[PDB]
Length: 125
Image (cartoon, rainbow, N blue to C red; front, side, top):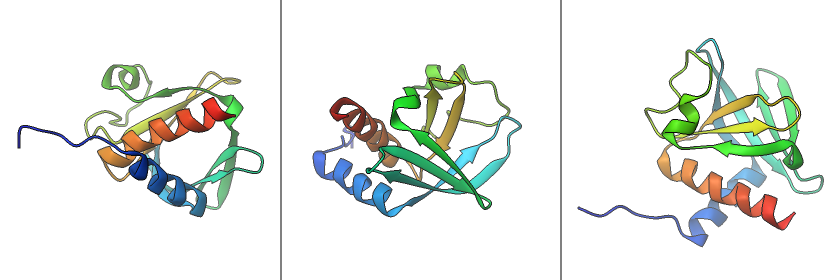
């Protein structure tokens, strides 16, 4: 087909449900390593957690300054990993440290929904 799908509210809500239940992602390390992780949203204190190899990192929503999702945005990240070629990555640009955590989702649709959902949680905060 000439045409591409676009994400709906249902798509975004489905990702929301999975984020609350915890979902599988990878983190892409600066040296090129890939960590298998669980990504979770905690709506009580409005924070994301990323849990990999028995270690949990908590990022308050208010520490997430920006989301890097476009090819050009992600090309600015200093790393040996390939963040852009699968167009499945969002990096959390953090306010305090100014550094970035790149998350790779299962594919383009989840990657796309995540960006919208995060905006929604941030804008409603």
